Amino acid sequence: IAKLPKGIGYEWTGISLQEKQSESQMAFLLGLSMLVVFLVLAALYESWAI
Amino acid sequence: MSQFFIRRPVFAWVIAIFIIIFGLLSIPKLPIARFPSVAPPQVNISATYP
Image 1 (cartoon, chains in turn purple, blue):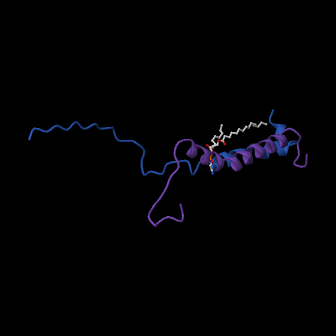
Image 2 (cartoon, chains in turn purple, red):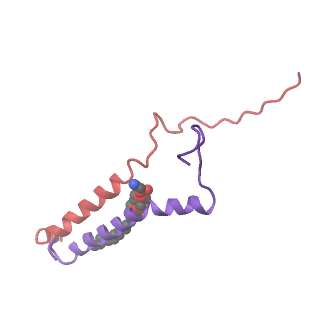
Image 3 (cartoon, chains in turn purple, yellow):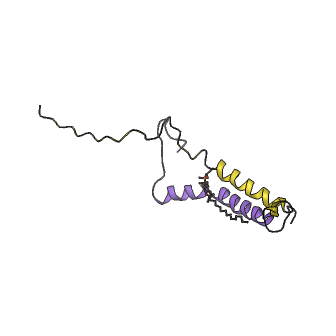
């Protein structure tokens, strides 16, 4: 699409827009899901090293 | 009693860290306005008989 004449945009729709949206969130959802368990384990084993 | 959080300081810090994180994930999520909807809502019915 970047080789087209200038002024021609594009968009994704349907199954593809819901696929591109699913790929931008994985690094955030894997970040929180590892940050939450690290927090809740410090609440049970009284330390940061464990 | 309330002597629980003297011998267990790490349990105190994660509750303080949890609401820092959840609060900072919500300041971009809040609408910025000058006033709430304090004024009563109006519904205009416009006719035409030229």
